[PDB]
Amino acid sequence: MKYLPQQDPQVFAAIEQERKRQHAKIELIASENFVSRAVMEAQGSVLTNKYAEGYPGRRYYGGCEYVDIVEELARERAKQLFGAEHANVQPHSGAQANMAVYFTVLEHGDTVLGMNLSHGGHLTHGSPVNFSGVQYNFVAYGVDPETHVIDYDDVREKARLHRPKLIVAAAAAYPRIIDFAKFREIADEVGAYLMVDMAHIAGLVAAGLHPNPVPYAHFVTTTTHKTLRGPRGGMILCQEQFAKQIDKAIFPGIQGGPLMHVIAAKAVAFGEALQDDFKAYAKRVVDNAKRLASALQNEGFTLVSGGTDNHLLLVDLRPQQLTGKTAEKVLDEVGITVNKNTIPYDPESPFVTSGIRIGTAAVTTRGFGLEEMDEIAAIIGLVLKNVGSEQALEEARQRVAALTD
Amino acid sequence: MKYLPQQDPQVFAAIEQERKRQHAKIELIASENFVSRAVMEAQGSVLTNKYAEGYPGRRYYGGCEYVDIVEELARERAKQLFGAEHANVQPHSGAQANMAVYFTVLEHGDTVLGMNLSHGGHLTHGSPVNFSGVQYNFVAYGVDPETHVIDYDDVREKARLHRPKLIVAAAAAYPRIIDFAKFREIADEVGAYLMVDMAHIAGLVAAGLHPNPVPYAHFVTTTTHKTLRGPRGGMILCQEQFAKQIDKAIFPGIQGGPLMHVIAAKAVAFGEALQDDFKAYAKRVVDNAKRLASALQNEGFTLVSGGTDNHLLLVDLRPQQLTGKTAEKVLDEVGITVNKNTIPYDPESPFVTSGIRIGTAAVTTRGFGLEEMDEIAAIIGLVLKNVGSEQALEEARQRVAALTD
């Protein structure tokens, strides 16, 4: 940076602390990643200055010729990545992407069927303190109490009992492949739309490592910042038949001016995702998650669902008589960043929990591989088996430092 | 830029076109401005990588120590700028800022009283194709048919008849000072909350050039990108008594992860606004708008309300037998960017209109002053009085080029 250090010493000092933090810690938050310098440059561009309500070639402001090129690059690259008929790259966030789909097809108080929030569902899939659960009547399907895999007979029974207008598939914390074909079959049986929120797995879908929901869903939502490794924001994919309605839901429905600089950054990220090296990266994410899962099991940890098919895993800490809160805190002390996370049928509140959620997207981006996964698992074992030993924690600290350099 | 040109030639070429465009044109879109290089650098930072749901010291992710410093800088500087008891700097946009306030105090179908959209009100103040008009029962107050000033007796009568739960004051296209004291008096009479949407005038308020709504309103919303000259985004100000409720409305209510890099950019912009030179800038914006208004009148144009008290003006093109659409198109041909805009009691649709909206915030930022205002007015006169003369339009083109260099 050149201008920020002089203009704002306070903001610059904090940014620099954060930059150094991102390098020093082992970042295992499943929803996080590290964007490229090109992506950041796009976000840091003069495109922030441009009002561009509307869509390419159909704006409500003059002078949009060039931001139009940018938005269309984003849309076309998204379509190439996911084989979707239509893309809307304007959503400010995952929240807004989901909000727009709900706004498109639902009226206030309509019934929606989503994944149980304490089994892996997201806040925006029906929490009673979120717009989703306040505006619409959410009911939930669960995972099997033993396998922790989605119970598709429960999906079906809930759908048939409650007659939802919309079924939501996808998750904030589900370590296995989701069967989109079965979701569409059930949706078809009850005459419900299917929305798939692929936010977590979007990069894996792009790389052909998770089945693509696009052929099965009426609407696919996603964030651009998780496994897709793009800027912070949202996106909606759908078939041409819903294009007009979806676009109108975003504007003038729920948003105003789009963030054109962020949309530029989305285009850049989609460009990166179209490259061969991204597919290799995504495979390493999945390989690393499996290896980390296996290595954690070797250390004596129980994993929700017994492993992983994707970028993320959940440790069930009950055998160690630890809460997720306790584990999260102590791992923070040694420089490993995880989330506490409810496990299916958790006896604890969502504020305490019996689990931790871990993902490999970020560490993979920094070049970590199988050997590093083994070491991460060994450090976690050292820490969680010796929470009362300051000597053990200092050893862990030193081993974390050795990994990050 | 260093990395974007190599990584993405297509995105870079379009960004560069846009950058050159912003320099070449006379940008009179009233809601636009040019942010500093420091603001852009903040947006282009690694803060995009950080999940930080929650608030400073009360997050749902570890490792937020530094993004917390950034968010608190934004909040504290906002409070200093506006004398508010509480700030929420997380809203992704003006849309989301307004959405959150509505979510806080209203239930589905509650009555809200806002400014007539064709008299200056914003889309989010009750359009039937916007969430505001779909989710809530909006009624409207108008301006006087002759003076084009808000009719406060109409505000009062509508309030007393319809018994709104909430009254919204502020505008996308109102060229005069708004009397917030009278709005609060009326709100008090009918037991309604008062929300002021100061998006357009926020920079003028910060500089003491428009009365501050903070002392009078329960909630103040704003965008950060108009006269405040900051990054694209929103903000909510309120008294401490509503702080918890407002914060909960933003998260977990209507948003997820905040855009921490944009929040950094907000802090930077607020830092800039706290400087003496910003107050001088804001006075020039207002001085320039008055001078441009006067100069347009000298050219024979009629202005809505007969002039301006702020950064923006509206030309009533009926005396020239022109529509706003026609004027917008022809001005585009010579390199002047304006919006078509409805005038109060417009005989034309919002898609055609009888007016153009002009603002001086952007040209003032680039260093334009009174002499430039005279020339802009003269060029507009030349163009709009000779729409059929290609020679006149080429002269205008050359004069526009002379202004921008």
Image (tube, coloured by chain):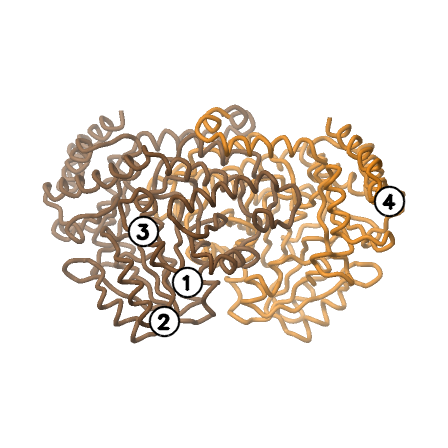
Chain colours: A orange, B brown
Disc 2 from disc 4: Cα separation: 60 Å
Looking at the rendered structure, which numbered label has been put on residue A385? Answer: 4
Indicate left or right for A185 with A65 as reference: right
* Viewer-nearest of discs 1 and 4: 4
Determine whether, in the image, residue B99 is placed left or right of residue A78: left
**Residue at the location (78% across, 56% down)?**
A354
The image's mark for residue A66 is: none
Q: CA distance from mark 1 to mark 2?
A: 21 Å
The chain letter under disc 2 is B
| Cα distance in 3D space between marks 1 and 4 | 54 Å
Disc 3 marks a residue whose amino acid type is Asn
- In the image, residue B103 lies at what x, y percent? 48, 63
- Where is mark 3, residue-wise? B212
Residue B273 position in % (x across, y down): 37, 38
Q: CA distance from mark 3 to mark 4?
A: 58 Å
**Residue A142 vs residue A333, the one in the foreground:** A333
Q: Is residue B98 above or below residue B394?
A: below
Tag 3 secondary structure: loop
Q: CA distance from mark 3 to mark 2?
A: 22 Å
Amino acid under disc 2: Gly
Label located before the other in sequence (1 or 2): 1
Q: Tag 1 or tag 3, which sits nearer the N-term?
A: 1
Image coords of residue A110 (percent x, y): 56, 71
Residue bearing the label numbered 2: B191
User: Where is mark 1, residue-wise?
Assistant: B132
Residue drawn at x 23%, y 40% is B331
